Image 1 (cartoon, rainbow, N blue to C red):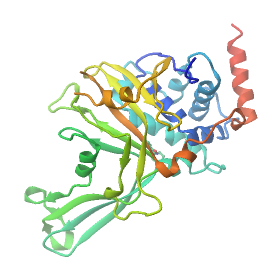
Image 2: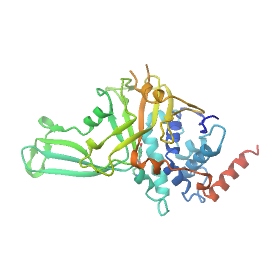
Image 3: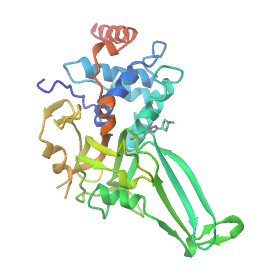
Image 4: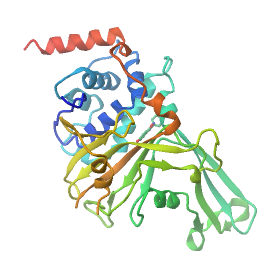
Length: 338
Ligand SMILES: CN1CCC(c2noc(-c3ccc(O)cc3)n2)CC1
């Protein structure tokens, strides 16, 4: 096991699930918080927080590939096409929603929003009359459009672009009646952990099957995002460091799923292809997954430069509470008696 990291078992069309599991396991600040969840009273079959702790503990200690059968059962995606019908951000939403709820009233409460929550302003500004509506919204990831864009920069430029509201799509200004208006979105804050979903998988009207766009789309190792802030901080620039590259190889519905990571944030990359984990070049993790063949990234994880050390803080064996280790060791001991 030259890498020091252990892989995950392939047990059905779980698809990206193993890529997401490794991506979250190496969000060290999240892993430590998951261990701390008060789970001793949970039922080892229905509880999703406990199943997530099991996978993370096995990923941290086992020399052999880690199984995920109890995880898949815990949140109930068990039909033939259950993972084909959803995408990675829904799975990530199902998981993170459960652990943040599990952290209520506990010492790691608010860890999910601290890591992933950003602040955003959506607006509608009337062009002929003085009226404006701003709604501040939270976001936990960003869906980036890639069709027609060459890189992450053009995808952000398109994200904050202004939309015209005229013709049939005039704005209902209420007292002012129908009005021509401008609609857009501004970024207030960017989170410590940036999850960017690249919109390569979409449905084409009038549809039957979902289509995957394999156009070339580039992303940098370092991503400066001060430009897209309404107001910047001299002591905390929005400089982001590429951490994970979730990759798909194959055609529209069918394909292989792999994740690349430099878990320490030191630019030393590894390929997490299911159970096999191996060192790879930086070029293979980033440049080779631009596309333009059928292998390319569909989700990216960036960590803010000033937050790298805390998000990726060290995780030892003593960061797992004793009651947790006793229960899982009891579980491994029970199954070993067959
Ligand atoms: C209610 N509260 C906030 C909403 C929801 C949530 N929290 O984070 C995410 C999320 C989704 C996709 C990602 O790629 C990363 C994060 N979803 C559940 C927790």
